[PDB]
Amino acid sequence: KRERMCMKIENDCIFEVKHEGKVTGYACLVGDKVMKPAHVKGVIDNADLAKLAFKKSSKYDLECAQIPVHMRSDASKYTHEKPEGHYNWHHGAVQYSGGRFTIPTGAGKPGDSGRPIFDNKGRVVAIVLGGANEGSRTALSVVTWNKDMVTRVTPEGSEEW
Amino acid sequence: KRERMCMKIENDCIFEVKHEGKVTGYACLVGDKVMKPAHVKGVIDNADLAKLAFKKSSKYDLECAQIPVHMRSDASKYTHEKPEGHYNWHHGAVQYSGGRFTIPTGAGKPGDSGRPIFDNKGRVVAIVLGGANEGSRTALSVVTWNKDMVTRVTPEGSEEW
Amino acid sequence: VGMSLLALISIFASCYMLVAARSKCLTPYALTPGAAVPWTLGILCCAPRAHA
Image (cartoon, rainbow over all chains, first blue to last red; front, side, top):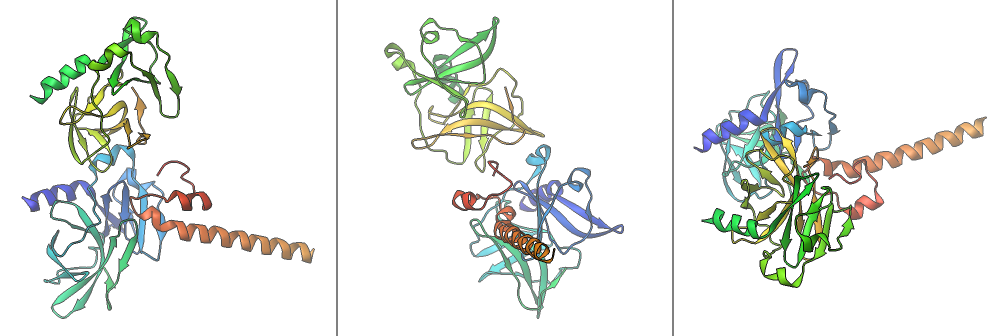
């Protein structure tokens, strides 16, 4: 049930980014803002999202823009509360312990940047940027939300996917 | 059950306004003040209310006047709390999500302005002014009440009904 | 000519510094679905005058 609704939301809220005919990253519809990591280069596979103006910021490595009015109902819902526990993700389940997003499997691959990390109730919590290979676990270089702030967490050795 | 006394209070707290003989909006009695939104033009289909002095305020798009003494028992009840969830309406149920009033059907049409939005217990929460086509949904542009202030919420792209 | 050129260069540099400071201080609020803090809005004017 949770996987099905997560996939249904992802299909309607995630768009691939094409550069030289190849996928490089994913742009997600969160709240009222299109979001995409800054380091990922390419064009979003959508005519409407193509001509939008993006406010870039290299400090947070993120490009944001205001979504068109006719797509406002096809966007996910967000949250800023991050209690301890487990969260869903398109490649399995992610573990949040002590402020760290860790991937037990190390299944991350370059080109998967921009995939949202989902909450239990289908809400979005954070957006992945890259992973740091710490033994059998992959610490996530992730960007999250405070009440009104964007904070970028970058564990040592992380590389941009 | 809920629809029954909902439309009964609607019957007791909604009067039509007609311009050139055709209905254009609805005026409702909330608390101790008759409310009719300013954008719609016409005359209230009642001798007593048509003779009252309506205070003008184009900033809030609302016209108010103090109800006569003998209509005080036919007025609804008000409140200032807006918990997340679902609320009632003449054309169905409205969804409150992230500070927005949204219509699941998107069947709102011009001439429906001024129809109150009810609570579960029959109290009034806001008044419908217009809507904005969010593709499959429509976000309601409504005027609500804070603890002691009037505030107006208008999503981008909204049109006045 | 030299004095006028120096004055114009200095004033353009100062204006650019003000613009850069405004844009860099105000950018993090456009990456959240949050408010603009009218206290900072009044001192630091922004393109969104009333919307968001």
